[PDB]
Amino acid sequence: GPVPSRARVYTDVNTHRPREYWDYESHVVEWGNQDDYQLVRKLGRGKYSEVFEAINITNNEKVVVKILKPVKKKKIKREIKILENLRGGPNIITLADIVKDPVSRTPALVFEHVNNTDFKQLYQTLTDYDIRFYMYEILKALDYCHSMGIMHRDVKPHNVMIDHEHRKLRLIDWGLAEFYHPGQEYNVRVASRYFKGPELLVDYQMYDYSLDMWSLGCMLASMIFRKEPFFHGHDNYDQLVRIAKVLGTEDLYDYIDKYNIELDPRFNDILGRHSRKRWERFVHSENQHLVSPEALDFLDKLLRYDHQSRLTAREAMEHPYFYTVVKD
Ligand SMILES: COc1cc(/C=C2\SC(=O)NC2=O)ccc1O
Image (cartoon, rainbow, N blue to C red; front, side, top):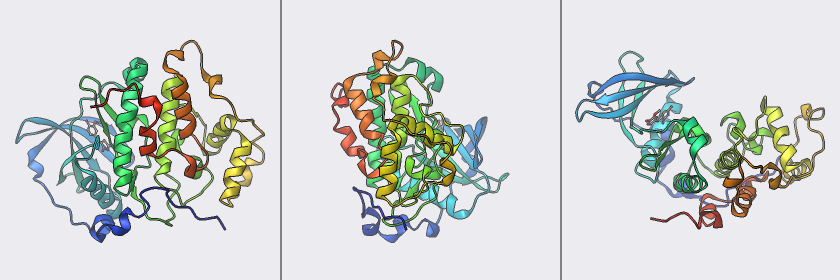
């Protein structure tokens, strides 16, 4: 069978926490007063929720309300428990309340409002300095939730809300997040296609916090190289081929061989043979103001096939890429 794997950091946080902390199926939701919140406008709709801008009429402050579409009580309690566990942590979105919506007959999560800048505006105008600054802010959030026993599993640009006017960042949509338990096998059907780690694409279930670091690397590559998304696969199989055309097929085989993993035979016809590329291949006159030796080395150290070889969030914050970022 496949060789087992454990996280190289924060391996035992949940074992030494009280069972109440991670046993989310036993969580008892504390309900607020639904009439405190008046919906103002629909902002979006996923497959698991509808999101609204609203006003809290007890302080006339803006909030955002996420009305969960009927999903199983464990997935609802999982998101709720994780948000409560992480509340107040650096750059974690704040769950302000939970109310029972009378129309949907499901829970509606009430978040602090973030006056976020247009995402396309953000992609187009962030500077070299901005990218380093906000990457550091994301790493604060990821080191926090990893240190708290939780992996996000859906790191992508649309879940990183940025109020550029106040240089404020919040990591949102914990609905795919999970507690990390050593030896646990997890569903590989997480994350958006372009941000899925090699472990998901080869069906390796015993993964950990390091999945988020691959996703973060995919974001970094899209920003410094001006190609969004960077690995642009047409499906989950082509997604791994896109990665292998950059990282090379020989290290892909080293990865699956280390964990005694077998590729889906459907790759026999599509994978090919590819050398590993040097990152300078993706530099050109329209992105070179965002590229530095420090940026390329940092990216190189996030985007490893072997989840065990990637920088941890804490290690990443030590990287020379961030030396120029003003610390508070
Ligand atoms: C879309 O504007 C916001 C969204 C959120 C949080 C969300 S939205 C979703 O689907 N899951 C979350 O945690 C919080 C503040 C906002 O201003």
